Image (cartoon, rainbow, N blue to C red):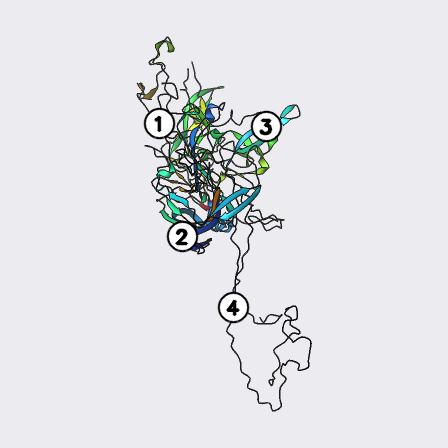
Amino acid sequence: PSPLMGGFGLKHPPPQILIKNTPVPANPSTTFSAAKFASFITQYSTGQVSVEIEWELQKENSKRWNPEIQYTSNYNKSINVDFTVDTNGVYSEPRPIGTRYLTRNL
Amino acid sequence: ADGVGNSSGNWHCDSTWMGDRVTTTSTRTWALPTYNNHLYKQISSQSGASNDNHYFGYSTPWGYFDFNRFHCHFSPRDWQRLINNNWGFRPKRLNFKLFNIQVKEVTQNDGTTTIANNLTSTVQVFTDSEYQLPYVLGSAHQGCLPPFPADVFMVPQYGYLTLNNGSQAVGRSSFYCLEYFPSQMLRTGNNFTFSYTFEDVPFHSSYAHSQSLDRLMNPLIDQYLYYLSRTNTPSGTTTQSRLQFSQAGASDIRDQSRNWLPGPCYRQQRVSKTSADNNNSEYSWTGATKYHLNGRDSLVNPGPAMASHKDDEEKFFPQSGVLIFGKQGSEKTNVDIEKVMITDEEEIRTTNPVATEQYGSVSTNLQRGNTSRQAATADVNTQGVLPGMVWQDRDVYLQGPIWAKIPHTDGHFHPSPLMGGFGLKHPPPQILIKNTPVPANPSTTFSAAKFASFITQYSTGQVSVEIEWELQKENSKRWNPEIQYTSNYNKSINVDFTVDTNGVYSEPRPIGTRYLTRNL
Amino acid sequence: HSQSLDRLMNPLIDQYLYYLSRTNTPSGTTTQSRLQFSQAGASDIRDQSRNWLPGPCYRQQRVSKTSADNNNSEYSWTGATKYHLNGRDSLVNPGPAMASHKDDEE
């Protein structure tokens, strides 16, 4: 049960966190009406969210002699630096980065 | 308690099943306007009304919180879990909470409606735990907690009726000022709570009898008792009077001696769901079943618990003998039959007489031979309680009421509410809530006239009701499977007891509780 | 009691229960059978669904304190309310507790 899109299969994954604004009714009628409220004060919410994850690492213990392939930035000059913002302050991710750079014997 | 910006409560809407108990908790968002412009107004029936419709009373600026319906606490899945597995249930205790109270000030300048917070205004809340106010709960009134937890509801206005001689009052009529009660004042950040314990009440009969009251015998063995089976014998070419007696068995099972009688009856007119089958006349009142009190006729609705119909007559129902619930979007006046859902009380026909038929027959004269007088009988359209009588109460429904207050009277017989539910001498107290009037700008010169100008404002908040119910577990020993409530597997445009594409919650049909079976 | 058994409701709020209010509708220039249902409020307060019933009754003949208003006959026993026991009639006096008269009939 490893996900086909990639990742860790969890029988009990991190739970869904559901958030919504409590409806605030607008001005009601002075006469009682059994119809459910359909007029509300327009509102939204803003705030900060923090996620902290602890990860366990499996340290490489290779005994190969020659150097390995490593992910690296390209030294040549460029208009924009990779994984930074441009003159519009727009953050971009130039390429997908996997994890399989070190080598291990079968 | 929590000033401005600190929540005074949380959303608790759920149910916990633990053995012989189920605790249902519900939270709703309510809106409370200003009623009567902070005034108490004497109200009465309009001039020209009939004597039966005459009334006198008072309208108060207060509202009240009503949760006297099962849908306010049980989800449809909760109801199905309750009725398919339990032979009975009853309420045990409840907890009530008001929290997250916001007072909003409304202003209107040059055609613009502006709403702003009022952090210093209060709302007055008190519970009538001494039952000193007229108990208007238990009259099947609108304004309850909506069945769907996501719906926002308006708090109904409180009002009561007192003695009236026509549209006028009498000296015995009582007036009640709700500000003469101690109430708790709540700003934004204050919360209200109280706990109530239900008195001991019988378990609701959430079962249908698998035996009939007239079929309680052993069909294999004859009785040792005799009954008069014949009154004459062939004599010559004519007849001669001669009494004969037989022991009753299976072939003459109707003549068997019995120990019990069917419950009391108050006959109702029979109406058919097929329109053409009904009489082409206006008989909703002339043919109605009524009781006479102080010169005024009141409709008997639904009246004593009686079976809606006999075998293979499901299209027939008593004229005012069953609860009729409105479908979603149904109007108030003269809606068609397809706009309403008519309940059925056929599960109690084992012990209760059919509503539209007579209780039985009694003798009216004294038969005698040779002048001769033949024996005569009459239908018993109304039957009071007799010794040895057994009956079942009216069923409760998901949309139906839960309880009612037993009137404070010297005598009463079987104080189960006729609309269905639990009769309580001390029911859950009325919870009265109103916005504290905030005077507008006063005159710089003193005026003894009472204030008539106020700042327009309403309040909104959350209400929580938690009820603990005791369960009577089914202990049946029948072999074949039982009837259970179930959803229909076939495909449909909409799922039952859900929202539609407009997000409108609807309850497609009334659900009773009598699906399991128990022997008589 | 300062309340009547048929006036125990809230006159401001309609009931959610329905009652059969009409049994026919105008059809063409004649009438056609058609059942209709309404929710009871203050205007049709007599049709409201109720939980209780008035106490038991054993009807008595009505006599007036104004002599001329009474029938000119001897009806103290023929019109009397009686119970039959072992072949003898006994007067029911005062009998089950019932109101002497309705409004404005002292």
Furthest toward the bottom, the residue is A65
Residue type of the residue flagged with mark 1:
Arg
Distance of label 3 from label 2 (alpha carbons): 49 Å
Q: Are marks 1 and 3 on the same chain?
A: no
> Looking at the picture, does residue B371 appear above or below residue B179?
above
Q: Quadrant of the N terminus of chain B?
A: bottom left
* Mark in front: 1 vs 2: 1
A63 or B158, which is in the foreground?
Answer: B158
* Badge 1: residue crowd in 10 Å (few <14, some 14–19, many ≥20): few
Q: Secondary structure at mark 3?
A: strand
Q: Which residue is mark 2?
A: B21
Q: Which residue is mark 4?
A: A51
B259 w.r.t. A80: above or below? above
Find the distance from the CA under tag 1 to the CA under tag 3. Answer: 42 Å
Name the chain under label 2: B
Q: Is mark 1 in CB contact (under 8 Å) with mark 2?
A: no
B35 shown above or below B381: below
* Residue at disc 2, secondary structure: strand
1 and 4 marks in contact (CB < 8 Å)? no
* SS for callout 4: loop
Q: In the rendered structure, which amino acid carries the disc numbered 2?
A: Arg
The answer to whether dots 3 and 4 both sit on one chain is no
